Length: 487
Ligand SMILES: Nc1ncnc2c1ncn2[C@@H]1O[C@H](COP(=O)(O)OP(=O)(O)OP(=O)(O)O)[C@@H](O)[C@H]1O
Ligand SMILES: [Cl-]
Ligand SMILES: [Mg+2]
Image (cartoon, rainbow, N blue to C red; front, side, top):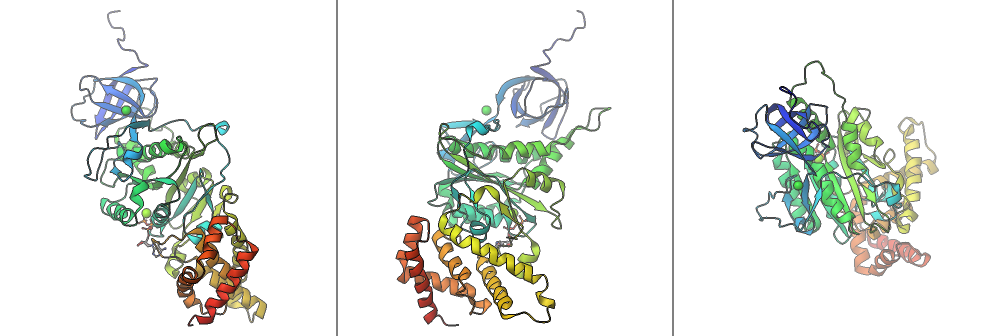
């Protein structure tokens, strides 16, 4: 036994490469992803991010300058935890839960691990309650239900963050705790977003997790897992949470950079790319739980950035496949002034449709049909030698409906208002106005409804359907408004 191996290879390891806040270890054969380890000599801790045999990747938490090749590493057998709960509402934190807003310590009473295994179907029940974004295009055509996974995808500067942040702003009074995860964005941009969340009153029920462009890849990589945990605190305690991952494209880039920081062991240059599994694990944690587990939910809104609208690229293909629905944004729409720049024909939300309230179902069906007919006709309309009156009417209706789907940033709309405005459209009441005046008509109409017909809005709101009685009154209110509207 003069030269026998001294260490336990399952729970103990040896640093074989260290630098730029990362280490690679021999041993630690039984370590799991996101498990804490300790560098014995220095007392510093780390978190496992890669389980390659005898080449385990470790994110060093804190001072890495003192860690040397040959140092012993020991499993702590604990998944790294973050503070979660009410104490984080109103706060801006990094992925480890440290405050970044100057408001003092968090003093959290609860903690959760950044990784858990997503519960199986036995623990879930069907999505049955809406998550109102307050954005007409989505709430009508791409309804989201609480517990689902909805992708927001499109090129840079198409309005992706805007949808997400407006959705958050709209959760005031909706009973939804919100977690906004900024991954890889510039500090300056993130600051602006936090300011808007503050200004529009969202921070009361919102936690912002930041790992900026200037933060290490390691923090960017941990960010969404920490954010999910923070949301799970509510989901698993009979409450509803929404977590925004902005964005998973930058997250994939950070995970890739982490892997590239250490060199490959000689004679093995290709370990598999499991970014698909990383995002799959993250998103499966969106859940609609059963009654025995409290009935709460966690809705996920991952964001993916495309290049040249290439939704066939790798990350896009991955996340499209592991989400229940997709909202597609496009630069052509954006540039034409169709904002939000959502392609409502291509976008889809399977699981949300049944959860959508009845009042909205009552107007979304016709909307969808009218837009379908419009887009068919637009195939050839501009090259038609002539179009009959009926066809012209269908085009006009369609142009009016598209105009109604335009909406300014930071202005999410109550569902009952969406309903009466979309009713006016689908029923033809904007057909005789110039298209350029639809926005104003909408603005003036809704003032008019509060001023003279609040009881209609109240009824739709309370009943969540448009009854025949209220429908008739609505028809008359619209006609009444038109009476005085100045074209
Ligand atoms: N509904 C809207 N109406 C008018 N302008 C909007 C709307 N939504 C977003 N914008 C504006 O369009 C621009 C792009 O928005 P945003 O940054 O949310 O898009 P993005 O896809 O997240 O871009 P990035 O690639 O920078 O993350 C911003 O200047 C934003 O203020
Ligand atoms: Cl911990
Ligand atoms: Mg963005």
